[PDB]
Length: 30
Figure 1: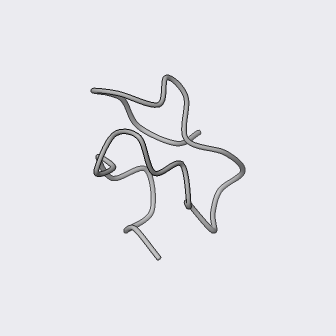
Figure 2: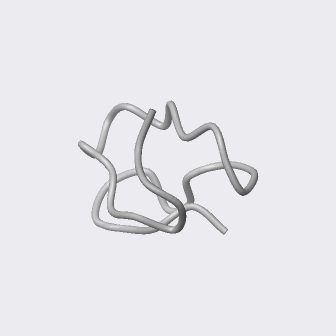
């Protein structure tokens, strides 16, 4: 479910950790 602080597919904010994927498109979950 997306690597730690790793980029996301974009429209899919399914980032387990650390918290959420923001921004959604072209961003990293922190």
